């Protein structure tokens, strides 16, 4: 989900772009500004919300010990989904 | 005689690189002319033996 | 459990001494 | 004034001086010590280079990481000049040749390229422009060097009206072609009077001209403290160097007297004490060794 | 407490305590403290006038024979008025034992050099001159050994900063490596790591 | 207040040792300018020696000036024997260091340092 | 033109000779030197590239700074660099030579040998492997291969 | 008068006072690799201070790791598990092979025998493959830690160590064929650098520098650490105190290291490799990601580090260059208050001036070879 | 428990004296050394053909750093600063904030690869396997600042080398 400033410089996933009058753009002259174009905030929004039949769900991020520490997410709010604080996968109680 | 087997292994290296042209190709690009089993080729043309 | 271990009978004997094999003719024979 | 160009630090290598300099001709004799004195303050120095990048290697230890940006440029390419100057707040011109080549005569090096750099720096919004003429630049001069350098001074002044133009007399240093020319000539003695100026004095004058807002639109004449005749100067060079490539234009310039311009400001008006030759001639001419000082006028 | 705990050696503890009593009563003119750690290492804390008589004793006495000087060390402790703690580590090959001899000095009191006892000390206390500033009297050639030749200050003092006061670079104007005041592109990030909870109640100091 | 001396019992013996160290540096400066092929004069090096001696001129403790004489003898031994290079001799002349702002107003202009 | 082709072929010739006869002077300062000794060891064998083992400093073509550059040795490094005949190159090997490394915040360590000498190739690692050092030497050979000395001479 | 030669800048400065061919005075100027390691250790945790020890004697990495680990474990009043101790002795003797290959082959290379250098550095490359397979790094493994070792042996590593060790004695035999009976090698080493036993004790020498002079001292025998009292080996003892007996002692120590490695491969026990005190050694990653206590302990050990109880130890090992010591002072915090590093090469290079008197200038490079000097540990 | 290297008294009968005289005059051990050098002349050398052949490595190998992702594209790094706390060189510089969906993510993740000691304490301190020290060792640069990696470079190294990094972690995580 990369975009471009009016200077022609790409904006990173942080939101960093130099100003037009900033001299430090001269480091990219004849070279390139290395950005990663796989924005993690856009890719985790592409994941579907997991409908589970429990009140409390556990997430370890997949892979068992290859994921993150296993946390427990409450799903009592029906207004909001329950988001994992590590991996950003989100859960909803189906009732 | 086992020197004849050495010379035949050299000649079959020449034959196994597809003739003298491919032999000299791998000689000047690789500094190495020994033949191997082609394990694979990636999407770039790098061949793995 | 599965762990890096020696085999059941252990490993074979490993040489560790000097082996300078004493080759050549005698000093009488070399003159 | 943008926040990234506010000065910070104590003026050392990792500091921020707030100077973003594009130094054309930085791979030469003056550019060496100018990029040295800029990089030790913590300036952003853009070095456009024409030569092999190997020949720019000595410019790389002169500043902190990312403080010298090297980029290709061509003197007849305004796109490369604009590519080099559009982020800078000062552009220094040090482009020069003592001889004319097959591709570049004195009009290309001293008129066309300085007017191109000054015009492109004017239309890129560069605040400060420093141009280096010669003290003996005259339209009616006998040498093609000084004629084209006077014409280029006039064109730089008329296309960048706030340019600081600097007149050095004859710059001596370790990599000069003034004392090293006399020490390797082993042409004669005439009635020519010279006051040669030291290279660190010239560099301090250029950097004080960057920092002084009163130096905009001025014409400075950087001269040494002592005027010498040419004959006893050359004899002093052969005396210090322990001794018993040229062209006729260089001979016309060695036999051209360094004019006195009291109406122009000098090194003292930029806060620079002009170092005499006798303190620094040993430092130059120690290389030529396999002394009573010269008489001033 | 068997598998994860280091086993205590009570025999060596008792032997080193008896030998510490032995040294303390043979040399009461200089011995100030004698202590044995829980991992059985003997420390003889002495007055600095007895550097030569104690170390010559331990080198030459038939029940000591500490012939080897393993290491000679200073420790800077700025809260003491004698901030430097000179540490001798000695090895007896005859009795297969180690002893530590500790003394003290401030910045201005010279310690007597022990080169006449152990020639091994010749560089070590020379290092103590370079790193801490402790002068050793009657040293044969006392000078710097590890710092640069024009180095100002003594770096292993705890009020000496981690990066120094000067740094070097090549300067092409003077064609020379030059020393300038230190500027770091990234400051060393000081970490405050100490937990505010007491770790070891056995080492609790009595309050005011 | 009863401390152990280093070499000098009082300040007069200490001034004697200071004076002999100054004599030795004064004799050594021309040889140092010659063999390191320095670009300074003998007068300039002797002025630097006088500056380094006058920098410590406020000290009234005999042990401190004994250590100053000891460190000056160490620097002199590193100079006579060619253990220093030309760079170490020229570090006394802070030539590449720009002059610091001295008055209040220029220190106000350049930054925050008092 | 004709002269442009001639100076292009002569650039290719002299760049071939200089990259296929690189003679290194290795500053064996610290642990990296050991790994340089593994790049001369028979597995990697720098000598088959034309890269001789331990050329003398007055006939060497590249200075390999392999180890921590302290303040006490930086003038000796600069002196040996100044005594090298041109064309001289500098490979910085390992983290302490590159930027100070594990001793970056030390009072006695030069924060990268690029404060002292101009550096062509930075070889990262602590230590970089002998194969990574050989990679850096081959990258230096590729950098020499695209030099344009006579073409820039013909265009100036 | 007599000639003064300043042999400028491992790297060493030497100030020779020669009287023709003879050496009258040898003044080694050092500090060319002084990096202030043990001041940097005071601003880092114990785990953070560990990789500085790889870089002191940088041909004896895991031995210095072992000495620092033994010092910290002594102050922590904990002991490593038995398999960790056997891995430490196995890799300590692999490390001893590495260092004595470096010692003997560069000592032969500096004298002029350049070929067994190349022969033995391929074996040294295979042992660096062993380091890389066990830790991920060829040289600075950071593998032996306070509490044990960082990670267990990968499967199939001990078989490859066996395949190395089964063939390495023939490599020692052909090194010894090139050098030991060679009259040119004997003329450069037999009457060179003779140290008496009393002067070697008095000058703080250790290791082969004692044992070449006939002193029957080895810290793996006399003051034994991890499981060296459970392995059987001999201690080579010299008779003349010269360069040649110290050469033979290093060759026979390679023999005995192969012997110890065979015993370690046969007697490797099962079990864990860190101490099972999770307030010292970090827990496994599977239980760090499952247990609350394990995650807290992981967090605190990798940010604060373990607190070490206050006190000072002098912990020494028989490193391949000699007695390698750490005088470690803890104030109670999670960072060392003081860490003096005793290196053997420091006292050995201090004794260089006595060892070189009455010899030639070509003998001095042989004496600097027989004192196995790495200036990382000399200068810190 | 000890042995005497070089404590042999040579035999002084005429047989052994003549043996040593024949060794002295006829250069026997020198011909032995020439035989050993000739023996290595006819061995296959240990030289691999770099760059076409590579030195063998393990999946534990500590090379170029990379920031990894979950199998959804979400980056693993949750800005806990354990890697920069444990970093013995202080090579890691981290700044963080909540991003637009409230997630705890870094805005700065810098690794100075010229301070870095390549010891891998960051990857073992990392609770979520975010920072890894991957398998690449062939990343020499021509300029010093190309080895001052920001977060974009490290995430591109992760996206570049993940197919290899995940399989190396798969081979070794049961030892961790
Ligand atoms: C016996 C075996 C060896 C035989 C001799 C070697 C065979 C090849 C001989 C010719 C090689 C090419 C010319 C010499 C090498 C020049 C390299 C170089 O740096 O050139 C730049 C140099 C200088 O170019 P420059 O002017 O850009 O200089 C840059 C250097 N600074 C900035 C320091 C001034 O070019 C020349 O000197 C040109 C020489 C003539 C070019 C060839 C003419 C035809 C020869 C047939
Ligand atoms: C065409 C081929 C020509 C070359 C042929 C040889 C090629 C291979 C050479 C390989 C080795 C090269 C090594 C280079 C360095 C050499 C060092 C060296 O050897 O130094 C010389 C060594 C020096 O020995 P040294 O000094 O090391 O031994 C100690 C000796 N003392 C105890 C006395 C001090 O030997 C010689 O000097 C021998 C010289 C040659 C003698 C030749 C044999 C003569 C036999 C005559 C008959 C005797 C019969 C018995 C008596 C009765 C008589 C009636
Ligand atoms: C008594 C006998 C003495 C003998 C002395 C000499 C011994 C060695 C003889 C030579 C041995 C073989 C050398 C081969 C050299 C490499 C040739 C080659 O392939 O070069 C390739 C290179 C680039 O070609 P390019 O077109 O870019 O390739 C892309 C292809 N798609 O293209 C080029 O580099 C351009 C072509 C270069 C050709 C060089 C050939 C070798 C010259 C050696 C000098 C001596 C010649 C013999 C003298 C004695 C006999 C007369
Ligand atoms: C008008 C036109 C002519 C102008 C004047 C030129 C006269 C002829 C000069 C020689 C030929 C010019 C071209 C030189 C080579 C250019 C192409 C080149 O570099 O090809 C590269 C190729 C090897 O590829 P590389 O990149 O090295 O591979 C990495 C390793 N895997 O390289 C190779 O395969 C080998 C290249 C060999 C180069 C030629 C042989 C040496 C030169 C012989 C003549 C000069 C020396 C005379 C005698 C000197 C003393 C013996
Ligand atoms: N005695 C003196 O030195 C005096 C000099 N001046 C003037 O000061 C200036 C700087 O002097 P100095 O350093 O000594 O001169 P140099 O000859 O040493 O360097 C001149 C610089 O200009 C570059 N240059 C030359 N011609 C061209 C061109 N056609 N296109 C692009 N770049 C070019 C050179 O680059 P490259 O290396 O690629 O050729 C070099 O970097 C000059 O203008 C000179 O006239 C004035 C008074 C006295
Ligand atoms: C080329 C560069 C070489 C640089 C050489 C550096 C040498 C530095 C050596 C420093 C040694 C000292 O400073 S010791 C001086 C300290 N003395 C004191 O504090 C006592 C006061 N001393 C003085 O006033 C001295 O001037 C005298 C001469 C002893 C007495 O003078 P007063 O009487 O009026
Ligand atoms: S970068 Fe690392 S391994 Fe290399 S010399 Fe430095 S400390 Fe030693
Ligand atoms: S490998 Fe070590 S030095 Fe490098 S970033 Fe990770 S923790 Fe820091
Ligand atoms: S330890 Fe891992 S999750 Fe924590 S800040 Fe570092 S890379 Fe991110
Ligand atoms: Zn999750």
Image (cartoon, coloured by chain):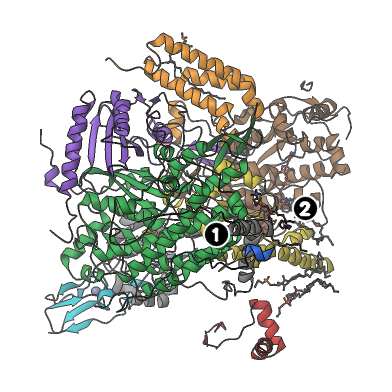
Chain colours: A cyan, B red, C blue, D brown, E purple, F orange, G yellow, H green
Residue D119: mark: none
Task: Give the Cα separation between the discs numbered 2 and 1.
Answer: 53 Å
Q: Decide: is H177 above or below B22.
A: above
Rendering coords of residue H143 (x, y %): 35, 61
Ligand 4: which quarter? bottom right
Residue at disc 1, secondary structure = helix
Residue D108: mark: 2
Q: Decide: is D178 above or below H105.
A: above
Have a look at marks 2 and 1 and say if they share a chain: no
Determine the residue located farthest toward the top in the rendered image: F12
Residue on which the image places disc 1: G37
Rendering coords of residue D175 (x, y %): 72, 41
The answer to whether I96 appears left or right of H247 in the picture is left
Quarter containing the C terminus of chain D: top right
Q: Is mark 2 within 8 Å of ligand 5?
A: yes
Label 2 crowd (10 A; few <14 / some 14-19 / many >=20): some
């Amino acid at each position: 989900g990369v975009r471009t400033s009016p200077t022609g410089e790409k904006v990173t996933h942080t939101g960093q772009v130099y100003d037009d009058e900033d001299y430090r753009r001269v480091r990219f002259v004849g070279r390139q500004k290395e950005v990663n174009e796989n924005f993690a905030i856009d890719l985790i929004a592409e994941q579907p919300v997991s409908q589970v039949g429990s009140r409390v769900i556990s997430c370890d991020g997949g892979g068992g010990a290859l994921g993150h520490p296993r946390v427990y997410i409450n799903l009592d709010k029906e207004t909001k989904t329950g988001t994992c604080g590590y991996c950003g996968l989100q859960f909803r109680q189906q009732h | 005689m086992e020197l004849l087997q050495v010379l035949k292994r050299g000649l079959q290296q020449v034959s196994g690189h597809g003739g003298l042209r491919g032999y000299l190709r791998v000689l000047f690009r690789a500094n190495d002319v020994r033949v191997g089993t082609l394990v694979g080729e990636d999407k770039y043309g790098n061949k793995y033996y | 459990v599965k762990q890096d271990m020696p085999p059941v009978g252990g490993y074979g004997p490993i040489d560790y001494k000097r082996n300078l094999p004493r080759r050549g003719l005698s000093g009488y024979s070399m003159f | 004034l943008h926040h990234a160009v506010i000065p910070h630090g104590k003026g050392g290598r990792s500091s921020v001086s707030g100077i973003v300099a594009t130094v054309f001709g930085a791979t030469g004799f003056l550019g060496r010590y100018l990029v040295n004195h800029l990089g030790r303050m913590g300036s952003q120095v853009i070095v456009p280079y024409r030569c092999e990048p190997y020949d720019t290697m000595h410019l790389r230890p002169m500043g902190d990481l990312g403080q010298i940006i090297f980029m290709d440029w061509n003197g007849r390419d305004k796109d490369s000049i604009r590519r080099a100057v559009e982020h800078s707040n000062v552009v220094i011109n040090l482009v020069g040749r003592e001889w004319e080549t097959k591709n570049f005569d004195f009009e290309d090096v001293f008129v066309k390229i300085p007017q191109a750099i000054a015009q492109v720096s004017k239309e890129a919004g560069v605040e400060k422009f420093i141009h280096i003429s010669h003290l003996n630049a005259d339209i009616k001069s006998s040498s093609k060097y000084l004629r084209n350098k006077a014409v280029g001074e006039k064109e730089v002044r008329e296309t960048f009206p706030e340019a600081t133009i600097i007149k050095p007399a004859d710059i001596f240093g370790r990599e000069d072609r003034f004392l090293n020319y006399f020490a390797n000539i082993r042409s004669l003695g005439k009635k020519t009077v010279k006051q040669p100026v030291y290279i660190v004095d010239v560099t301090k004058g250029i950097i004080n001209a960057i920092k002084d807002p009163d130096a905009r639109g001025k014409t400075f004449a950087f001269v040494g403290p002592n005027r010498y005749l040419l004959f006893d100067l050359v004899q002093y060079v052969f005396a210090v160097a322990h001794r018993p490539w040229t062209t006729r234009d260089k001979v016309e310039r060695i036999h051209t007297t360094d004019r006195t311009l009291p109406h122009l400001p000098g090194l003292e008006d930029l806060g620079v004490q002009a170092t005499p030759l006798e303190l620094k001639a040993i430092e130059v001419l120690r290389r030529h060794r396999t002394v009573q000082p010269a008489k001033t006028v | 407490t068997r598998p994860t705990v280091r086993p205590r050696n009570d025999v060596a503890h008792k032997q080193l305590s008896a030998f510490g009593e032995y040294v303390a009563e043979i040399l009461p003119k200089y011995v100030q403290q004698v202590q044995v750690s829980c991992f059985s290492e003997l420390e003889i804390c002495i007055h600095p006038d007895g550097v030569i008589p104690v170390l010559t004793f331990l080198r030459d006495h038939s029940n000591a024979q500490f012939k080897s000087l393993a290491d000679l060390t200073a420790v800077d402790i700025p809260t003491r008025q004698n901030r430097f703690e000179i540490v001798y580590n000695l090895l007896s090959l005859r009795f297969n034992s180690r002893i530590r001899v500790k003394t003290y000095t401030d910045e201005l009191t010279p310690v007597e050099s022990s080169v006449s006892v152990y020639k091994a000390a010749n560089w070590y206390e020379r290092e103590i001159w370079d790193m801490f500033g402790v002068f050793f009297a009657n040293h044969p050639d006392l000078r710097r050994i590890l710092t640069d030749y024009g180095f100002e200050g003594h770096p292993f003092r705890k009020d000496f900063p981690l990066s120094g006061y000067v740094e070097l670079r090549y300067d092409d104007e003077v064609k020379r490596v030059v020393a300038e005041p230190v500027e770091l592109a990234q400051e060393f990030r000081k970490f405050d790591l100490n937990s505010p909870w007491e770790a070891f109640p056995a080492y609790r100091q009595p309050p005011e | 207040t009863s401390v152990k001396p280093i070499f000098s019992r009082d300040m007069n013996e200490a001034k004697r040792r200071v004076r002999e160290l100054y004599r030795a540096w004064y004799r050594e400066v021309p040889n140092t300018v010659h063999l390191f092929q320095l670009d300074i004069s003998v007068k300039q090096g002797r002025d630097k020696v006088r500056e380094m001696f006058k920098k410590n001129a406020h000290v009234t403790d005999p042990r401190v000036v004994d250590l100053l004489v000891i460190k000056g003898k160490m620097e002199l031994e590193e100079t006579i024997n060619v253990w220093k290079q030309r760079t170490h001799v020229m570090r006394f002349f802070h030539e590449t260091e720009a002059p610091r702002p001295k008055d209040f107003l220029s220190k106000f202009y350049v930054g925050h340092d008092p | 033109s004709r002269g442009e082709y001639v100076v292009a072929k002569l650039d290719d010739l002299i760049n071939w000779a200089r990259r296929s006869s690189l003679w290194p002077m290795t500053f064996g300062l610290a642990c990296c030197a050991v790994e340089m000794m593994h790049m001369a060891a028979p597995r990697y064998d720098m000598d088959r590239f034309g890269v001789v083992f331990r050329a003398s400093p007055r006939q060497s073509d590249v200075m390999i700074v392999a180890g921590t550059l302290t303040n006490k040795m930086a003038p000796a490094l600069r002196k040996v660099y100044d005594q090298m005949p041109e064309p001289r190159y500098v490979v910085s090997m390992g983290s302490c030579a590159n930027g100070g490394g594990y001793y970056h915040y030390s009072y006695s360590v030069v924060r990268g040998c690029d404060r002292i000498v101009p550096v062509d190739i930075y070889v990262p690692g602590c230590p970089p492997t002998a194969e990574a050092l050989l990679y850096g030497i081959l990258q230096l050979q590729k950098k020499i291969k695209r030099e344009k000395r006579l073409r820039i001479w013909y265009r100036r | 008068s007599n000639l003064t030669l300043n042999f400028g800048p491992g790297v060493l400065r030497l100030v020779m006072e020669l009287s023709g061919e003879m050496v009258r005075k040898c003044d080694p100027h050092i500090g060319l690799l002084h990096r202030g390691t043990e001041k940097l250790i005071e601003y880092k945790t114990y785990l953070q201070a560990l990789p500085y020890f790889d870089r002191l004697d940088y041909v004896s990495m895991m031995c210095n790791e072992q000495a620092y680990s033994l010092a910290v474990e002594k102050l922590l009043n904990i002991q490593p598990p038995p398999r960790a101790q056997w891995i430490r002795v196995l890799f300590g003797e692999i490390t001893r092979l590495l260092n004595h290959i470096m010692a003997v082959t560069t000592h032969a290379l500096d004298i002029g025998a350049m070929t067994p250098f190349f022969w033995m550095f391929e074996e040294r490359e295979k042992m660096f493959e062993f380091y890389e397979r066990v830790s991920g790094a060829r040289m600075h493994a950071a593998y032996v830690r306070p509490g044990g070792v960082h990670q267990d042996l990968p499967l199939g590593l001990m078989d490859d160590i066996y395949e190395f060790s089964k063939n390495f004695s023939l490599r020692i035999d052909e090194l010894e064929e090139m050098l030991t009976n060679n009259r040119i090698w004997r003329n450069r080493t037999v009457d060179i650098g003779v140290v008496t036993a009393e002067d070697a004790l008095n000058y703080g020498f250790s290791g082969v520098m004692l044992r070449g002079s006939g002193i029957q001292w080895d810290l793996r025998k006399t003051q034994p650490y991890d499981v060296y009292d459970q392995v059987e080996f001999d201690v080579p003892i010299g008779s003349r105190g010269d360069c040649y007996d110290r050469y033979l002692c290093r060759v026979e120590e390679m023999r005995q290291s192969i012997r110890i490695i065979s015993q370690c491969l046969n007697k490797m026990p099962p079990g864990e490799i860190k101490v099972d005190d999770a307030k010292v050694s970090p827990p496994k990653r599977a239980e760090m990601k499952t247990s609350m206590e394990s995650l807290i302990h992981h967090f605190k050990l990798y940010t604060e580090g373990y607190q070490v109880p206050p006190g000072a130890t002098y912990t020494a090992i028989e490193a391949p260059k000699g007695e390698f010591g750490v005088y470690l002072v803890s104030d109670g915090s999670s960072r060392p208050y003081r860490c003096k590093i005793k290196a053997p090469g420091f006292a050995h290079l201090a004794g260089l001036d006595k060892m070189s008197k009455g010899h030639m200038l070509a003998d001095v490079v042989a004496i600097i070879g027989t004192q196995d000097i790495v200036f990382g540990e000399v200068d810190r | 428990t000890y042995k005497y290297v070089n404590l042999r008294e040579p035999s002084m009968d005429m047989k052994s004296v003549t043996d040593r005289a024949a060794q002295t005059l006829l250069w026997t051990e020198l011909i032995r050394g020439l035989g050993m050098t000739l023996s290595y002349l006819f061995r296959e050398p240990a030289t691999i053909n770099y760059p076409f052949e590579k030195g063998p490595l393990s999946p534990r190998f500590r090379g170029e750093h990379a920031l990894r992702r979950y199998p959804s594209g979400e980056e693993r790094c949750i800005a806990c600063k354990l890697c920069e706390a444990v970093c013995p060189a202080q090579a890691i510089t981290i700044e963080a904030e909540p991003r637009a969906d409230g997630s705890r993510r870094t805005t700065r993740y810098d690794i100075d690869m010229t301070k870095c000691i390549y010891c891998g304490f960051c990857q073992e301190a990392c609770p979520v396997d975010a920072i890894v020290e991957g398998p690449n060792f062939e990343f020499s640069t021509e300029t010093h600042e190309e080895l001052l990696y920001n977060k974009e470079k490290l995430l591109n190294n992760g996206d570049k080398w993940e197919a290899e990094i995940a399989a190396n972690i798969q081979a070794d995580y049961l030892y961790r």
